Image (cartoon, coloured by chain):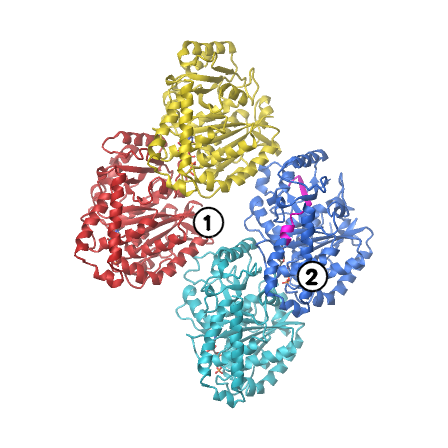
Chain colours: A cyan, B yellow, C blue, D red
Amino acid sequence: MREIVHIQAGQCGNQIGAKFWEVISDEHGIDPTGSYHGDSDLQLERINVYYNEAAGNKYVPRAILVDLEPGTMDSVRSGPFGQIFRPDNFVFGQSGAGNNWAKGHYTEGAELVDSVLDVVRKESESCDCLQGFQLTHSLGGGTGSGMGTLLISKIREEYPDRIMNTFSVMPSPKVSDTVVEPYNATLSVHQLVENTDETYSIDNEALYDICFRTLKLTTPTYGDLNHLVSATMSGVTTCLRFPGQLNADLRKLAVNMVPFPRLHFFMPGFAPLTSRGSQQYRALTVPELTQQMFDSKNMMAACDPRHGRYLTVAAIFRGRMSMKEVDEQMLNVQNKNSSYFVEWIPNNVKTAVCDIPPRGLKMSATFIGNSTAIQELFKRISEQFTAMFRRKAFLHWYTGEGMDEMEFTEAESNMNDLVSEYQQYQ
Amino acid sequence: MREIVHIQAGQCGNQIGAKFWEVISDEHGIDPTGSYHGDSDLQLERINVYYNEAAGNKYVPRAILVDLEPGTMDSVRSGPFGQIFRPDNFVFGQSGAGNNWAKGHYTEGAELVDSVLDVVRKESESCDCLQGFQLTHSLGGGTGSGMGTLLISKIREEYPDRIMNTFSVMPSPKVSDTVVEPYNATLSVHQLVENTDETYSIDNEALYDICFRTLKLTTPTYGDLNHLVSATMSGVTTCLRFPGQLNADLRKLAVNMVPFPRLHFFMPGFAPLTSRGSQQYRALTVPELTQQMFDSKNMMAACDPRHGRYLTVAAIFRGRMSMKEVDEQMLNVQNKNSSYFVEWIPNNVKTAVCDIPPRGLKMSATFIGNSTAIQELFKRISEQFTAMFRRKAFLHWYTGEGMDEMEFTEAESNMNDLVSEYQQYQ
Amino acid sequence: RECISIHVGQAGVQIGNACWELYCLEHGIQPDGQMDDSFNTFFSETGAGKHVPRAVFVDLEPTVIDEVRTGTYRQLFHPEQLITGKEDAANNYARGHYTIGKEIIDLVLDRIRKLADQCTGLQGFLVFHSFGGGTGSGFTSLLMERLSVDYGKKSKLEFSIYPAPQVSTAVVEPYNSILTTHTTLEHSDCAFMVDNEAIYDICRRNLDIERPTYTNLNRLIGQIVSSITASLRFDGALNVDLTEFQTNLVPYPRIHFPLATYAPVISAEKAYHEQLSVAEITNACFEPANQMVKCDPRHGKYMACCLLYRGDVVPKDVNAAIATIKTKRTIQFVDWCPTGFKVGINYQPPTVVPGGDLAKVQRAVCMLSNTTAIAEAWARLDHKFDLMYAKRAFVHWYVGEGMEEGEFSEAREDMAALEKDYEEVGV
Amino acid sequence: RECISIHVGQAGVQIGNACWELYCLEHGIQPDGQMDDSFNTFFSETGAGKHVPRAVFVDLEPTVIDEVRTGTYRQLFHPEQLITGKEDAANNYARGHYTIGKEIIDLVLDRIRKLADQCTGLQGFLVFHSFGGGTGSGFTSLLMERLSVDYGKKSKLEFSIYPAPQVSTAVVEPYNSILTTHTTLEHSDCAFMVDNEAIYDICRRNLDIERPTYTNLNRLIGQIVSSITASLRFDGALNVDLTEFQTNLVPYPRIHFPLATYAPVISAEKAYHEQLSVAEITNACFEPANQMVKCDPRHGKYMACCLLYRGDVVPKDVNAAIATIKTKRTIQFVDWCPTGFKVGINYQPPTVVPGGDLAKVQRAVCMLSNTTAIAEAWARLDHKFDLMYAKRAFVHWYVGEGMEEGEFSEAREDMAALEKDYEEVGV
Ligand SMILES: Nc1nc2c(ncn2[C@@H]2O[C@H](COP(=O)(O)CP(=O)(O)OP(=O)(O)O)[C@@H](O)[C@H]2O)c(=O)[nH]1
Ligand SMILES: Nc1nc2c(ncn2[C@@H]2O[C@H](COP(=O)(O)CP(=O)(O)OP(=O)(O)O)[C@@H](O)[C@H]2O)c(=O)[nH]1
Ligand SMILES: Nc1nc2c(ncn2[C@@H]2O[C@H](COP(=O)(O)OP(=O)(O)OP(=O)(O)O)[C@@H](O)[C@H]2O)c(=O)[nH]1
Ligand SMILES: Nc1nc2c(ncn2[C@@H]2O[C@H](COP(=O)(O)OP(=O)(O)OP(=O)(O)O)[C@@H](O)[C@H]2O)c(=O)[nH]1
């Protein structure tokens, strides 16, 4: 009932998705081998929405892992829960992309798309009725940016009505771990803005800033950053995984958050966030979390929300709590800070609650916001794109793969249009 | 039949009223929980004039407790008879007045009057026919002086014919427990002199002097002082609570004591008054009480009655006694001391008797007198008002709450007028 | 006397599991499903020593249905009545009415008809839903149009939860209510509205419960809809059936939106210190803040109101109460219907749930009062709707379902057609 | 009733670690951080069985912060509240306010606002600092200007340590006080002053402690500021809230500098030999040498004073004491406010620190008294300032920071504007 198929494109997609099955398997009570040892009977109902039942009380996930280099598949297979994944989904080529969007989208990826398209035919048929696809990729690089967005277009041609949710992490000016970030980003958003109905824009700068102020981690690795983003992907897909007083489907947030088809780039966030050295000195009540919810330095995007205005926001709470004090809190943030909300909508806040919180915690929530502050991120990368594109630097490799400079100019026409769209409703 | 609603404004109003229900509940035989365990059937008839019958043979008072600080409500709730009061009447704000008449009358009290005006509508509808309101407040401070006198004006607008009896305790020169006494006193008496038809002026100096000469209390706390004033409030409202040979309603004293509408500031007093070490050596007969009744140091006001002349006085006796010797005693005090009585009235004495005395005592009485000696109290506070007002000291906080210095001058115009009214008939 | 209930959406099932919690306790029915004529109007005789409820819990999302199937009231409800869908409406009137509704209404309508066939004294229906949601707005609009053409003459009670002035759970809920009201106006006989924030200050002020949930809310709403049908269950000195509320509340065929208010709502420790009587409850219900809908009654005039009581209440003191309320000039009744009073008494007192915050009381009262105080709400809903309609926001989903601006324009002018006659009769 | 405290500079943290030492002992709070309504105004309930203090210890130099973080009260204070800077103010009002202040005030102000959001009964604030230092003069002037424009209406208790006539720790401390007083004059509601040398002869004469430290000093100052807020913590016969001290002490908006004095201050062996009563303490506080500020009261006249007591003290003997004090012609009350008495009683007695030099007493008293006796201090501070200002000494650092002679000239004439009205009201 309302199944979801997980896709993991690119090196970041395989790693960010490996932690997604890590955290949700704990609250569901799934063994590392695949069996079930949960404590509550409520965890057994909606296991089909992400896993497939097997013999011997064993369960396997519907994870479509795809990449062009075999190193990421071997590392994930040797992980904590690497053995639970089925081997036939681990499709992979031999040669990597080398951070080239043209190779993994036209020439190198087209040799691999024929092998993975037949796999999703098997998984889409095994479920009763698919709800939406939860893809994970990164705009940086060529594999996840090129081959990841390719199958977005192919699947949308098959399913012109199903949901296509993606958790896309974008580049940033200060944190630049690759020289080809603006070109890979500019060509990817041309397709994501038209094809996908939902998009969660994540920035690596905020993942470093969020871990400095409140977690106080002195040596945070990639595994620490994955725990933050994986919890947001789990929090959004929790209402259709456990029962609650008001369950919100993934599509019910799409109807509330997406007032126009292109305007779907969301601001992810998470609460509570407190270090081990200050977890005891904090109140887990709803007034404490709500103030930290809409804090300027809480979301997973470097853009300041004070420089924009929220068009619509959501706070899907999670855990046993009284919804009376919730509604007063969402009333206060929109009333006390009405200048930072659009006047042409009466209420910019969505609500949702669940009864069974995660392990170790009592109450929690997850933030999803579509705001005008994101246009500062799309324009700065466009300046990076426009600075190098005007001299045609680092484009001769793209033309070798059958590309043309006209498509780069057409992608710029999509880039400068969507930033002006945010300027209209600001 | 002829019900009374008790209001308790200010900190002193809540404390003075808590002892009023303490003493009258004893003679009526009311349990601390609310049940009835009286010894005589006569106590059951006129219980409705102050209490409401409830289920399980339970009785609840019509006490409208109002204050701006929650400390007085919690202390009274934990008192001896704190549980008998109904919880909904305990209305209270968060911030105190800080001894500011302007805050509790225009800005801070106006947020609370809308909550208490609807409560008295409920209690006024539950009774058959209200006789008059018995309010209790203090001129000292801002809460009882500011918010207490506000609802005096609002209730008089609703009931332009009912009785408004108030037991107002005033400041004094030697006993000054607050710096803002003359300003709070001068603004309150401007309204009390026009709105209320009855007023009982109590002074803390007399309450300290009355316990020194006759009770001989070596450590008299506030609880000892409340027993004196609570007995006077009970003695006046006793004829319409038990039967007697000559019952005098609260309004029947007002018709006899108030020859002019502003001239209604009365002198309260009580007898018998004897220490535990000299109770056996005193005679409880009427000639013994009557000499102690009109003694110069007996009333609850610091002003010497020898410096004035009684325009009218009342002695509502209480207990089984022969009224022949009563009338001879009231004849002797007016004839033997005719210089201390006005010649333009033939008889300045009122009489009233009751059959059932309080518990522990056999015969008692209560004094109510309107005399010209009270002008010495109104002029000395006016001198305190005039000394500080002429330099506009301690008025800038009043102007912050929307007030003006013109109202202080208008209050002085009422102050110097009423003291000259006493000088006319002296 | 029989009547069939139906619950739709997330709002319905929380009212379903709560309102049916006290009915089985009222008739002494254990939760297992077993223990003479009082329970006939809501429970049938299942052969021998077993009952079955006369309700259908339809919902597109099965996240609530499996909870009830795995809940404590498993053996009570029939497994066929717990209808399940395939995917949620997503706060879309279009998706819950046209795409997902048509492929399941053929099963629901046939299920309603076969249960209604064995009835003999079916008085009417009562619907539990909420226009602010998707399933409660889209699917409820489908069945109401499709059964009204079939039956038509029978009565209907639409128990809809409306949005608050400032409080709101979603952002598209004005679009859900503006469309469904265009269809609900001509077919719904009478709709009793409920507001979500109006319950918040009631329990906070009166019941002094500072962290309740929906389970405390629906226990009160379930008690309110039990009192309106209590005359049919148990005997009464002045009984009123389901057709009584059609005439004395609906003077015009389009003005069929009465307010509601209920009293006494007193806590456990507060009940003993406060005297329960007819006078204060008759004054408490007319108090404006004591209503289940936050709308100022002083901004309009009252058309008609019904005073249905519970417990051992003599018929004389209730007449003196409404007579005294007539003398109070703080309220003002409309000259078009001055004698808009309808007294009703029932012998069976209010029940009490074990562990519930509501206290036991020997007498109670429920109120349905038609007035012109609701026109400010529809005026407010139209103004806030115009802010989003100007920018054409949240429209691409509806036309993406199949709708268009035409019916949206017909829905806007319909409220304008409703604004004029509320102001006209208010004169 | 709630109130948020803030400590600034070296002077603040020695007041912080000392004044909070007795509060946790008053409420029976162990140093680890755990053990119903008395502790609410200074300690919040952190979920279940854990407390957290309502204070912010800001300081540019972290030499004190790491000591407290590595001290014994580590588990009590929130680690986020212990704010740390980057480099000290160097006894420069300009460096602690403009350069170093601006790059950290954005973090401190946001920290103050988020803690004040969850408050409901926030009466006001109380600031601990010292104008003779750099951080206490510069950074405190920044936040007081920046929060007053935000909140404004709320009250503020400035507990500032002033310089002595002949005793002095630094040489630039007149320049630190002359600048900050120009800004503190219009925004600070009331500032209770403390003198450093005034404590020296008190413990030497009365307590006969001939080698104490700041730990003995701040334990007394922490007890003084605990008594002024004691009415809000525990019940009392005549309670006074935070707004009471703003009206009955500040008759004019610019004359807002009351003196302070405290009694009894008796040692352990001396307490058993001396009779504790109301008469001697009521005379001892009005004694001039028994004050926390070395200023001759006989050179002026008193405006108004408050007699707030502690412990089991009946209200009658205190009235007789102030009555007898009125008759003493050795003092002289001003004719503009002769009835400047404000009695206050509290039931909770004074506490005692284990091992401290202060002895247990069943009754105590604290005094705040407005008078014209401070004008001689400001006259002295202006004369000594003129010696350095004429030669333009210690000026190249301030203009080296960014200042100039204009604000220095405006600061000089501001005291001249304060000198005239103190002499005017003194008539
Ligand atoms: N939030 C996270 N971001 C990651 C993680 N790993 C990498 N990244 C970020 O994504 C950027 C590029 O994504 P990838 O690591 O997948 C590069 P890719 O595997 O697609 O190409 P090749 O490895 O060269 O075959 C990378 O520079 C990081 O900024 C991760 O685990 N979590
Ligand atoms: N005859 C009595 N007089 C009292 C009693 N309590 C106080 N008082 C006197 O009344 C004076 C002021 O009255 P209150 O104590 O009520 C001060 P209030 O509560 O109104 O303001 P705040 O306490 O500051 O909120 C006070 O200074 C006393 O002289 C009492 O119990 N009996
Ligand atoms: N008062 C009250 N309202 C409820 C309750 N449950 C749901 N609601 C209403 O439901 C609305 C939210 O939309 P839902 O009805 O839950 O919609 P849904 O059934 O989850 O399906 P979708 O609209 O597709 O998301 C809110 O505005 C509430 O007013 C309840 O238990 N009590
Ligand atoms: N009475 C008293 N005064 C103190 C105490 N601690 C510091 N001071 C005051 O602090 C002043 C000295 O300057 P500091 O406050 O130490 O300045 P700082 O924090 O070290 O920073 P800089 O001014 O930049 O050097 C003295 O004039 C004292 O009056 C204390 O414990 N008791």
* Front position among marks 1 and 2: 2
Instruction: Say whether mark 2 and mark 1 are on the same chain.
Output: no
Question: With C363 as the anchor, is D242 left or right in this view?
Answer: left
Label 1: which secondary element: loop
Q: Where is residue C195 in the image (x, y as percent from the top left)?
A: 62, 52
> From what the image shows, is residue B19 above or below residue D132?
above
Q: Can residue B81 be seen in this view?
A: no
What's the residue at 21%, 59% (across, down)? Answer: D395
User: Is residue A113 shown above or below B261?
Assistant: below
Left or right of C10, for residue D391: left
The vertical placement of D424 against D160, above or below, is above
Q: Where is residue C280 in the image (x, y as percent from the top left)?
A: 63, 37
Which of C167/B271 is in front? C167
The residue segment tinted magenta is C360-378
* Viewer-closest of A284 and B90: B90
The chain containing the residue under callout 1 comes to D
Task: Locate residue C74, reporting x and y percent.
Answer: 69, 58
Classify 10 Å Cα crowding around label 1: few (below 14), some (14-19), many (20 and above). few
In the image, is residue C362 part of the stretch drawn in magenta? Answer: yes
Q: What element carries label 2?
A: helix
The residue beneath circle 2 is C410
> Mark 1: which amino acid?
Thr
At 75% from the left and 64% from the top, the residue drawn is C105
Horizontal side of residue B344 vs D317, given as left or right: right
> In the visual, does A1 lie left or right of A380?
right
| Residue B83 seen by the camera | yes
Residue type, numbered disc 2: Glu
Residue D120's disc number:
1
User: Which quarter of the rendered picture does the C terminus of chain B lie within?
Assistant: top left
